[PDB]
Image: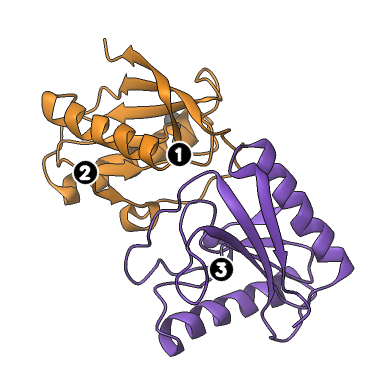
Chain colours: A purple, B orange
Amino acid sequence: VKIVTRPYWLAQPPIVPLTPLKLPIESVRFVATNTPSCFTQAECTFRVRLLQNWHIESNGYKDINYNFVAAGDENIYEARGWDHSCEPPKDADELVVAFIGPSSSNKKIALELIKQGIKLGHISKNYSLIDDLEK
Amino acid sequence: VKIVTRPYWLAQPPIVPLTPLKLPIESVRFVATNTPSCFTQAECTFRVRLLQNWHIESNGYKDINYNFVAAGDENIYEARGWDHSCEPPKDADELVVAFIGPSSSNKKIALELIKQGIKLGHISKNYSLIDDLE
Ligand code: NA
């Protein structure tokens, strides 16, 4: 799976340091961002930057409040990543994968990411998948 | 343990994507950098930037070829970090911790990092410690 890391989408650092996530992760959650779809890396990159700015400045979060973001360009964007927890109202012990324009396509990509996470020991073999994409 | 993350030492990104590191890590290796000691974060940041440039440009590595760097300013610098393995001749399953001006000071902080890694599930409770400092 192709991950667009933080530097490649011009991420700013967390405004203050994030809290470490205990591994292996035992719960994964798929959520919808309910922001405009995007279909190229340039377009999706721009959207992720905006998401981060909004989460930090408008919401008062320390950083973009997901671990990863699947987008319409079929890329996974690194958000808080494997090792740091999201903050409330998200669960600190879940890997949160957000979706910009959820679809059959990027859902399969996100599932591939989970499979890799399991193989690499980031995600427990005994994990729960919480699919909130319909809401 | 205070970790100076990549953005805070002005790291460039890997030249190309790195290989993922499997967890839990079963082996930690201590290696010497053979670079001048540094005693302030300003000075150590400069040294770590220089190490990364050296590894990428002179050695042809994709990125600084350590996971963490322990320095004389008593800081740990995030290099490849928890998630990505070092490339050859380093082992793809080890956590490589480099030392700038290796000392009893450096070692204590490095051991704290390991203890933190174990608590967080990054490192096996039964990890091997490979000492390449000499
Ligand atoms: Na050279």
N-terminal-most mark, 2 or 1: 2
Please name the residue that numbered disc 2 is placed on: B75
* Residues tagged by mark 2 and mark 1 found on one chain of the structure: yes
Q: Position of residue A119 (x, y in %)?
A: 69, 37
Asked whether, in this view, residue B83 is left or right of residue B103, the answer is right
Q: Quadrant of the C terminus of chain B?
A: top left
Q: Quadrant of ligand 1?
A: top left
Name the residue nearer the viewer: A117 or B39.
A117
| Residue at image coords 11%, 40% | B39
Q: Which mark is residue A88?
A: none
Q: Position of residue B128 (x, y in %)?
A: 40, 16
| Residue at image coords 26%, 40% | B47
Q: Amino acid at mark 2?
A: Asn
Circle 2: is it few (<14), some (14-19), or many (20+) Cα within 10 Å? many
Indicate which label's residue lies in the foreground, 2 or 3.
3
Q: Which mark is residue A66?
A: 3
What chain does badge 3 belong to? Answer: A
Q: CA distance from mark 2 to mark 3?
A: 28 Å
Q: Amino acid at mark 3?
A: Tyr
Report the number of discs: 3
What chain does badge 1 belong to? Answer: B
| Residue at image coords 33%, 21% | B30
Indicate which label's residue lies in the foreground, 1 or 3.
1
Please name the residue that numbered disc 1 is placed on: B121
Instruction: Relative to B28, say whether B57 is above or below.
Output: below
